[PDB]
Length: 135
Length: 135
Image 1: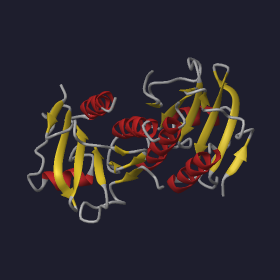
Image 2: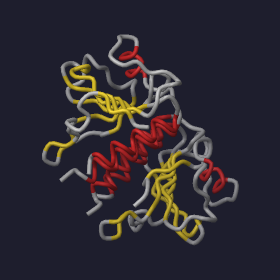
Image 3: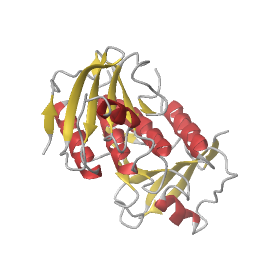
Image 4: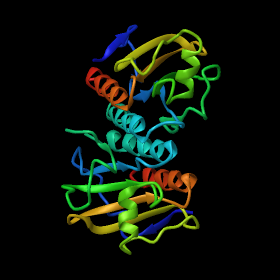
């Protein structure tokens, strides 16, 4: 199910005990993808030996990010994921499976982790896979 | 802003290092309320010295809950919050402020913490107040 594109295992969400990424939720999306986001945020907090960890895709841009971005939701869900799709950084449709996709430096030099699939279910599977990998 | 109804300070979300509540997200709602939910889940995870901590309001009922429920979203957002509103346990409208409302035993004997306000902003304020209180 879960396609690991890029070096996902190398994507660090914690450095010491301080989070290295925002969790960007699709504002134009289902409450499911962001249930995923909440579970991911729970995982990160668990690993947190500042600011809202979770934000909306209307409150962050790739060009202005000062840290890594975990995009939760596909192009139909997350505006930033769509921006990445409208630029060939990611190719994702309704037919796309659960996907953890690292785009290097897509956010103002900082790496991006797209956690998304074709539908809500696939996004949730990808989030769950990320949680399993973080342990 | 944040109305503390009931004994909110006494609402324990962690017992030792294992979460005592679900975080129930309004499926029929804004991605903002559940950005709140994700931030709350981050807080809980931080305090976590099993299952998805965050769920949707379509995946849990009050009558079947086996633990505390943190409802995120007002009656317009969270189906369980509406059920509580359609029963006088909570009274919440567009005019309602940011609110942390403990309903004792509303979920099959387990207590419920409504984290919600009149609009998205108020829900987020209530979530932030809960986070500050948990520390």
